[PDB]
Structure formats: structure tokens, C-alpha cells
Image (cartoon, coloured by chain):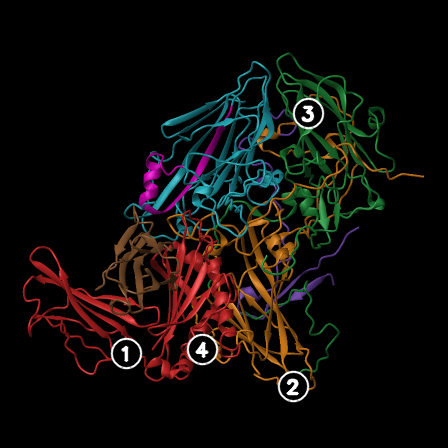
Chain colours: A purple, B green, C orange, D red, E cyan, F brown
Amino acid sequence: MGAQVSTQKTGAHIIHYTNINYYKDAASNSANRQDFSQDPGKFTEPVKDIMVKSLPALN
Amino acid sequence: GLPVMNTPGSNQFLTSDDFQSPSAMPQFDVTPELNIPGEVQNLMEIAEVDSVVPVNNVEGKLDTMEIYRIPVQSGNHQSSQVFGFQVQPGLDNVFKHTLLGEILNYYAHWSGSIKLTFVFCGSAMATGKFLLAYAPPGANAPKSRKDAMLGTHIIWDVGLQSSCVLCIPWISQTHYRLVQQDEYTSAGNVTCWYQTGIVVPAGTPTSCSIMCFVSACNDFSVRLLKDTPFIEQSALLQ
Amino acid sequence: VVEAVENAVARVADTISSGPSNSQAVPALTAVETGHTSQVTPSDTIQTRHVRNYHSRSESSIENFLCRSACVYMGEYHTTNTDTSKLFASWTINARRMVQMRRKLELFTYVRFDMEVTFVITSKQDQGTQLGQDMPPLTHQIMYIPPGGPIPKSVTDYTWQTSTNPSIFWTEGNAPPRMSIPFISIGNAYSNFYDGWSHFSQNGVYGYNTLNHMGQIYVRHVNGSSPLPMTSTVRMYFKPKHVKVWVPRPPRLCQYKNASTVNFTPTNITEKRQSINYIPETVKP
Amino acid sequence: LSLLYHLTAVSSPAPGTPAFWVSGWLGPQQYLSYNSLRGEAEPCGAWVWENQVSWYWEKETTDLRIKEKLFLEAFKALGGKGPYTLQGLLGCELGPDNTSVPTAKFALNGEEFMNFDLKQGTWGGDWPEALAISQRWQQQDKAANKELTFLLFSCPHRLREHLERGRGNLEWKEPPSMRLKARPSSPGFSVLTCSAFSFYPPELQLRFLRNGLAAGTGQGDFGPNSDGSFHASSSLTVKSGDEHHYCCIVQHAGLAQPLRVEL
Amino acid sequence: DRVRSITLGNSTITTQESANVVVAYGRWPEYLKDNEATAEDQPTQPDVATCRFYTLESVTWERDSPGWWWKFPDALKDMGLFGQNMYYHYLGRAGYTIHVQCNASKFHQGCLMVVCVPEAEMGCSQVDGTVNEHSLSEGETAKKFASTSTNGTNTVQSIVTNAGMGVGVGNLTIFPHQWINLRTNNCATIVMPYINNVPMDNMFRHHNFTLMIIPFVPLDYSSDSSTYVPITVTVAPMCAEYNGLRLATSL
Amino acid sequence: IQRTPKIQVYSRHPAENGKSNFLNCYVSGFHPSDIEVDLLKNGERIEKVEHSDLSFSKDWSFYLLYYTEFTPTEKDEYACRVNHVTLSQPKIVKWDRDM
């Protein structure tokens, strides 16, 4: 009946849950607490030419 | 209808919950999405950017740009330390208002290694060499170069490349440290010394400045969200 | 039917082993003039062991950082008075009167999200020379007025019919009321900062008050009662969800002065110490 | 019958002068006087001749103080250089039996630039200055509802009270005194002049007649007196002759019929 | 590796002491697409008469200079045909290329930060007050920071340690920026795309971004060296578009 | 943004000698808030001079009235002097015993 089963947040060194949506608007849903994506190079290396970090930065 | 039973925690308002809720504007058509540059997905992306450190936070210079410059001159000064401070990225006065420091003050636990970049801002005719040393906790701060050379150090030579990186590695008995640091979660300290001195030709200034930037490495993480102690009000309308 | 969804856990990078070195590779030398931040790990400067790191950056995600409910408004209103203006509460909607959520949101230039609103209403009996009465439970009405709709003139106005405005009726002793709101803006995102004017001649109003325009809230008692005076207090709580942000900014350093402008009194960069070399002694007998 | 309030505020005041003052008018003559150098209203003692015990004068002191602080706040929203003057006309006027009509207009440096609308309860104009001042007044977060009730429940109530509280002070009616004389002019000409003194109702009609044929009204000058009575004047430059024929006819409410005036 | 050339329109710029080129967020300027537009009329694209280099007037770097700032646009409103197209249209859109120039001998020393801040909303010297449009910008002439607190009237609180925005000046490295170190380079280049929460906007009413130049290490020399050291700024629009043609507005 | 004043000097009661009377100087139609009004008895500036409230008309133009107590005499004259922002030199209006 339109059920979503997904894993729970655990640690490392029965583990999943179930969700059903009841309302007609997507703004009524719960938060998206499980999206983990990264992209630091947008702010840390915004340069036109690549720098390989083992060669001198200039010359 | 269906027989049910109410459990403890019913009819309470917890701030950190997330349940579904009824919408007050049914079938509302939102504006389309625009592709704007500079999207952020994780606060750790901000802490990985360098920012200038106010190392010269002495009395009388708290409101001038001189708070950012480390002075260094020519002549025989091998016995006088250049600078030194504690590694407390969220508690010490020299770090708590930087980007990394301001991000950490929203959390309670931190872990990972740090990067300190140093740039020399003298003339092109000046030369010199410096020793940058990090000491893990367990003893007092080194009071000479002979003592400082025993820890994790780098010898920086000034040339065409003007910047040198000192990486402070994660060396701890626990997996995390407190942003509000005590004796038990100490991290050590950092010091700077002359390795050979500064030599200039005739016609150049004899005094120079060094600047320091701080950032986090790619093994850095924080946890246990909390409120920050820097902002406050006494009434509404502020 | 049931559909399985997979969630990818993202952990930090490991530490690789490295040994001695003598070569022309110079990872520790760079130039900050390029505007580029160096990417060097301890493996490039010292000798390191190999570590399998399991730590996760899950609590620093934007969703987990902003999806917390905080107070944004607090107000009072009476059941009976001689003013006819203290009998209801009303205000314009914005997250700029309380400094915590304001500072948290102002870390970014553009924001876009849905909202979850929760109200906390508490009543009390005013001090007086003669107490003692038998009053039924109080009921409260909350009305949201979009920009352009008519305004109530009193607590007995026809406008309370809420024929098209959304409204909430709540009785004391029950769970707090709560409702969801979608992203309601004429632009593509909300703006915390606006460096412009309202009029094409470069004058008028400067700043944020040119782009808010999102309605008001009114709150009243529905009993019209209480031979003895009582007082109610309402607190509002916002909680964004399904969030996106753009163009990070440096955090606010000076204290806030008002809700409309960004004016400030100049402050110091940080606090002082004894010298540029001073470190306190902690290992003493 | 209409109750009105003239409010004036200046940005750079002269030494010894108030920065904000109000005058109240119950029809043709004044009954109130307020300023910021004192902070309280003062009657004329000629409308009710009875000091209402702190319930009519401590009631107006408060809203006048509110208007004072509002008008003084209205100057910190203007980024311009030169000095400023803010004028306001606020009041009401009762209809046939009920349903008072309100009035609220404002002027900046002598130009009407904004007003107050009731269905939204907001100040509004079209200039940039109007929008700036209206925004600053609305950030006061209680000012809209207070003026909104000032114009629909306070001034009509005060008007209905005033219409029967000093009713004898509404039938002020005095017959004006005529002084028609003549004086020389340029060679060949002479200026007649007919005046009228101490007439309570402001309406008054004058005209010039040669013998029985009207020769015009001339130029009517009007001036108040220091007690509420009025002074009117009319003059006409004619030939040196016929000066013993003219008879200015004056009609007034305090006159039973248009008395003729003779030199 | 340190020589560079940039050609736009009928203008070209060369350098022999370049560090690199910063692209603000990894995004180059682009034209507006069909699936993200809102205005229905056909736009105009001059494409060579507006996309070229304009040079502002120079400032004099002295021993004690707090810094300077310009606002964009409204600094190029009198620059050839890019300014004329601004007066006749209601909506406009463009990216930019910024080039800052300052040279000195190998016996001088100093360090400048060159940063572009999107939507630099500024605060007044009187906390309960308002700023002027003249207090925010002067077209081609630069505004000046101060060393202490300013009092003035309707002016910007321009002490340099707060950057007129109430933040720490040492954190401005979060924005797209470069440094000019008198011992390393003599020029800085920043390529900026169009950044806004709407697809197009009016150019007279909204300052899109502010360019700030701040010396962190003061200038210094000794006893026979040149004392006059100027700084020059040169800006070029890219992918300019306009909509809403009518009679020319006036200020 | 400037309006030059308009002066009218007159008397309350008719001007026959020996009888107490009120001399009035009425200025109207000027839009600064500041103006200098004085009374003169053949140039002699009258000391005891009272004023009225500074109100305005519906065209947002100010008016003010000074009043003094006197008695008419065939010999002496009366005048009203005014200095104003619009006036290069102060205007002196001589009182007519008829207007």
C-alpha cells in the first residue's frame, strides 16, 4: 500500500523502518534527514588551471 | 473502532521531532527551481576554507588591522620566540571567531587534523628560515629552540613560493574532543622560532610581517548540536 | 506493494601509511595569492600509520543543521480591558525579531524551504483584590491574513468569519496546534540580504523591508468572558524542511540593533591576552 | 459641524520654539492648543466653561503625546539634507444623523504626499518619502490600530458630545458694524471702502452700487480677531465724481435684512 | 606559466606576473535558457559593443590607507553603450571579468586582498538612521574605508575592521577573492557569473556585487624608492542581455 | 518650495479717537515655519504685543495674527514690520484707519 522501507542510522565497529504518506501535498512530508553529499572544491579550489599539489604552485 | 492504548509521550511538543502535518494551503503551485551558483550541502565545506587568524591579540590592537600581523625583523634575535599559542579551535581567543571556530561553536564534539598556512610578506630581496613546532600535551610549552625541535616540526625556507603549511595531526586517546576544552581533552601547543635569521641588502626595510591562516583537513567532523554563546538579546525587536 | 529505498552512508577519508622521503616533490610549499586552499594531509609531511576511519559527517548536513524548531515571536493579550487594543494580538511574519534563528539563517545568502509552524499558548489569572470564579476552559482563534486582505478592527468584527483565510480553533489542555506551509515566494528563493532600493530613483526604503510581503497573524479569545481579568501569551515556532541554501557568508560578529536594518556598533575582533608568546603553565607540582 | 486637528512638526527648530504643536478646531473657531515644550492640552474656557475632571484633558494628552513621538520619529527615515516640515490634518465630520466621515492627510514641505486608508488601516502615498515614512510608522507595531480607532470611535464620540455639551457656544451671532468711507486716489479717482467688524459667522456678502445698479464687489479681505469675531473689508476705485451716490449693501446672518450703508 | 592574455571585443590585456584565474563558484557566465526564463519579449544582445574592457580611475596607495570599495553595476552606467542600454531597458543581465593592477619594485613590500561580495548590504553610522545612495556609491570614484569609528550623518559605518557589514574582516575569504603580494604578483583576475534569486533584474535599483580592496600589510619602502604607487581596476561585462525597451529614465 | 507671505493690517473696532481699540496684523500664505513680525508706533517698536497660534490653511500655507491694544489718534500712525526668508528687506505696512 505504497510503503517505503529503508535502513536506520546505526554505528559500526530489524535495522530498517517503514513509512507511509497520508497527505496529498508534498510539503506535508517529513524532513529528508538522510541525504549526505559533498562538494568542497566549489569553494576550496575555484581556479581555472589545475594545481596538482606536488609541484610548485607558481613557475 | 479499533482498540488502542496511549503510551507515555502523548500530547507533548518535542523540538527535535519530525512528524507529518496537515497543510494550510492545499494544492499550492510553487515557483520553479532556479540553478543558482554556490550551493551548500554540508557545513564542513565552509570549515575547509582558509581564514586569517588574529594571533597578535594584545592590549591596544584589538580594533586595528595590526591584530593580524606577526612582526619579524633582521639582526641577532635567535633567543626570542616569534609566537606561540594553544591548540583550542573553539575556546581560545585566537581561534574562536574564525570560520572554523565559529562553526565549531555550534557543536559540542570535534575530531580531525588541522592545517595552518603561513605567508611571508617582506620584500623580494629578504631571505630567512623559520622553525614551526607542534607539541602534544603532557608537558609545558617549550621555552627554547632546543626543546621545540623535539616535537613535530617543519623548517620553512623563504623563496619564490611564499607559503608553508604546518599540518597538526590528530593525536588523542579519545575519538573526539570537547569544543569546551578542559585539562582532560588538551591538544598541545604551537610555537615559532628563528632557524637562521633575516638578511636584507641596503635600501630595503628591516621589519617584516607574517600572516597565518587556519583550515580543516578532509578527516574532520563535528557532532552534538547546541546553541552558540556569542549572540544574545535582552528583549524583542532586535 | 512495498518499495525498498537505499541510503548511502558517507564517511570521512582514511589515513594511508607513508615512510621516509627525499625528492623534489614539495607538497608543503604553495602560494595563497591564487585564492586556492591547499589540500595536504598529515601523510605528506610526517610518517603515519594506516587508520580505518568510521566517523560520519551526518550532523553537519544542512537539513540536520536547520531542521530544529525555534521561537520567532512572543505576544500577550487580555480577555477584558479598557483599551480594545490589548484584547487581541497581531504581527507581521518574519524570522528577524529573535537573534538565534536569525543568526543561524544569515549564514547563507539565499534560502528556499517549506515550513512547519507550532504555537504554544498559556493563560494566567491577573492579580487582584478579589479572586475566585468558575470559568469554563478557554478557546483561542488564530487567523492568518495574506497580504491584501481586510484587517480586523476589533474582537467582534465580521472579518473573523474566515471565509477564505485559513484559521485554527484550539482549546486549552490539549496538544499544541501545528500546521505546514509551502514555499510561498514570488521569486525563486528567499533572500536574507538585499543591497538595493525600493524606488527606481535610488531612494526610498533600503534593504530587507522591500521583499518580505508575506502576510500577518491575528489571535483572539472566542469566549468574550471572564468577569475577572486574565491574560494569555502566545509563542510561535518555525521549523524549515526540504531546505536548499546558496552563497555562504561570514557569521555575524556585532550584536543586532533592530529587526529591519543591519546597523551595528563597531566591535573588537577578539579578546586580548598577555603577549604574543604567552601560554599558561598547566603541569605544576 | 466638524472636528479637526492641525498638527505641525519641524526638524530643525528655533531656540525657544516647540518642535511639534497641535491646534484643535470645532468648526469655525479653535478650542484646543498643544505643544511639546509643555506636554499637555489647554482649552479656551469658552466652549464648556467647565474643566472636565481629568477625563477629557488627560485623555487627549495621551494621544497627542503619541502623535508627537510619531511625528518626531518620522524624521529619522529621511536620508536627505535640507530641513523638513511635516503637516497633518486629522479629524471627522458627522453625516445626516450618524456615520461620521473621517479625514487624515499629510504634507511634506507643503505638498500633500500621503494619507491613511481604513480598509487596510495603513498609511500610503506614491513618493519614495511617503513609503519610507509609512514603513517606519508601521514598524512601531501598535500605531495602525491606535489611529484606526482614533478616527472611528474617539473623534465621532467627542463630536456627538460637543454638539450638546456647550450648545450655547454654537449660536454665536453678532450683527456686523458698517464703516463706509472714501479716500483720495490718483488724479481723477477716489477709493471707497466699506468694512464690517465683529460678526461671528464667517459668511458675509458685500457689493458696490452706483445709485441702484450694482457696480461689483471689489476685493474682499478677511481677518480674524483675537476673540473669534471677524473683520471684513471691501474697496473700489472709481472716478472723483458720483462719490455721493454709492451705497454698499451688506447682507449678513446677524442682520435681519440687507441694511444699506450711507457715507 | 605566469604570462597571460585576455581578449574581449576590441580590447586586450596582457600580464607577465599572473598567479592564476579565479572562477567564482566554478561557473562561467552564460545566456538565459528557455526553460528558466519569465519575460516573453525577444531580448537584445549587442555582444561586442558592451562586452569589452572599461578602466575606472586610479587610487593612490599610501602608507596608511584603510581601503576602497566600488559597487556594480552603477559604476559602469556612463561607460559607452553598456551605459546607454541600461537607460533604455527595464531588465538587464550580465557576468563580469575583473582585473586589478598594481606594480612596484623588488624593494617595496605590501599585501592587498581583492574580494567580490554579492549583495553587500551596509549599515549606517547612526543605528536608528538611514544611509544615502551617495553614501553607498559614487560611480567611477571609489569610496574610502576609515581607521576609526565614523560618526557623520546618513553615512556608512566604515571602520575597516568590520567592513561596513558587521562581520570579521578576516573571514571575507569565504567569498571569491585573490591576494596581491608585492613580492609575488602584480595583478589579480576574477571571473564572476550572474548571481541573483531571480533570472533578470533592474540595474539602477539593485547593486549586484561590491568590489573591496583592503591592505592587510601596509606599504613600505626606504629612502630613495618611488613613493607614488597607484592601483587600477578594469572590468568587462560578458553575455549581456536586456528586456523591456521604453523611453530613457532619468536620475 | 517657497511661498511669500501676505500682509493685512486693520483694527477691530472703528477708528474714532479716545476709544479703546484693537490693532491687528494678519500674515497669511507663507511656507516656512519661521517669520519675524513686529509692531511699530511711528517706528517705535511696541513692547506689549501678544500673538495667536501658528495654524495653517487647507493649501498647507501658514497664517499668524498679532494683536495689540491702542486708541486711535489723528496724529500718530501704526505699522507692521515683517522679516521673512522670501523678503530681501523687511516689509513695513502702514496701518490705514479705514482698511
Task: Determine the CA span between mark 4 and mark 3.
Answer: 83 Å
SS of the residue under disc 1: loop
Q: Can residue C209 be seen at all in this image of the molecule?
A: yes
SS for callout 3: loop
D56 on left or right of F23: right
C-alpha distance separating marks 1 and 2: 63 Å
Q: Quadrant of residue F58 in the image?
A: bottom left
**Tag in front: 4 or 1:** 1
Any magenta on residue E86?
Answer: yes
- Whole-number angstrom distance, CA of label 4 to CA of label 1: 35 Å
Which residue is found at the position 70% from the left and 62% from the top?
A16
Find disc 2 in the rendering and name its residue.
C135
Q: How crowded is mark 4: few (under 14 residues within 10 Å), some or many (20 or more)?
A: few
The residue closer to the viewer here, C3 or D61, is D61
Q: Where is residue D220 in the image (x, y as percent from the top left)?
A: 20, 66
User: The residue tagged with tag 4: helix, strand or loop?
Assistant: helix
What's the magenta region? Answer: E76-102
The spot of residue C120 in percent (x, y) is 64, 70
Instruction: Determine whether the residue tagged by mark 2 lies in a helix, strand or loop.
Output: loop
Viewport quadrant of the C terminus of chain B: bottom right
Labels 3 and 2 in the same subunit: yes
**Residue placed under numbered mark 1 in the picture:** D174
- Which of the marked residues, 4 or 1, is nearer the chain's N terminus? 4
Residue C68 within the magenta-colored segment of the rendering: no
Q: Name the residue under label 3.
A: C26
Q: Name the residue under label 4.
A: D153
Q: Which of pointers 1 and 2 indicates the residue nearer the eye?
A: 1
Q: Which of marks 3 and 2 is in front?
A: 2
Q: Where is residue B103 in the image (x, y as percent from the top left)?
A: 67, 47
Q: Which chain carries label 1?
A: D
Image-quadrant location for residue C135 = bottom right
